[PDB]
Image (tube, rainbow over all chains, first blue to last red; front, side):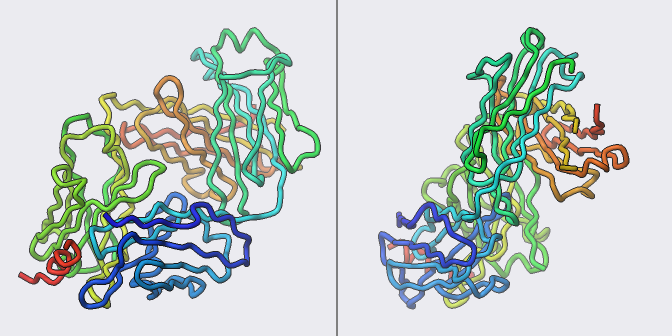
Length: 217
Length: 219
Length: 14
């Protein structure tokens, strides 16, 4: 095949700045009539891919003119001259000269100011307790940057191995993240303990913030 | 407007076959070649094959020759991909797309279907269980739905039949030790509106036929 | 090569 190597693979960019993505080809892309079938696609979080640039430099209708593509032969480039918040996504190049192939994808993330999370803690509902299991949920809302440390402490004892977290994609408007940690216990264990805390460490926080409750209030 | 309509998420057992469709509209299906693209979860895109609906001629990525078979029904403006001998590796999202043309028209994929997500599994389908994360207490409170122990993916969550969009955060599902998926949706709301505005999450599972509406009230 | 084979495919009008 033809391998489309893209550089860089991760592209942290500020809003307003320029951003470039290189796409190198193992073979020269040029059919007999002289056409280079190199395209650029953007996939925004939770969406189909969408065409940006085709035939190296022709801009698909609807694409803002901030997007341009240059290059010849085996080197190609995509430029975003002024980056908006809603340009976060994965950027793929694509060739149709030989058996069609994509590049690995470039993940463009918005660089924004530090923002400390709002932290919320939710005991298990009674319907869940009447069913034998107990999920305790710690919420971190609208924060930046991504890395956060959430520690569970039951009766002031650090938990390990019984929590799971997931983090939303970067929001296309405020460029922040949100995270949920879930402490999962059996009903019987949940009732051998009083204080349930989650403890949040983050760059936006001078001191770790903990939220807690007492089983049964 | 040009639209490609692909069916919703499908669950198939290993070793069988699956035929997914793609309805073209806003244009005449025979005027444009179609590509099919595969995207495994958290992975790049991959070209499967190209069909010319006018004369049914096909061309395949070599890695999919024997696995995929593109056809087209002109009369009903529908293109089809059949996959055979399904394994766990064939669990992915499959896109049909329209090719602009050739030469100075470009060979690009200008319109894309929303994609058909395919889970290959011997496991039986299971509906979710929806529990409330009730609020307790600057004028900003949080509430949400815990959607627990469903299979396969995905489940979708709206709030108040989609009349509550700003503030929501539907997390990516996490895979628990049970082998079942679990996810939560939250939304941030004013504290003053808790006794006055009702909050209902519309959870929704298409692989099973489950559809649950939970009122999230403060305890 | 495959580049030519793809070129005949796209221009095929039978």
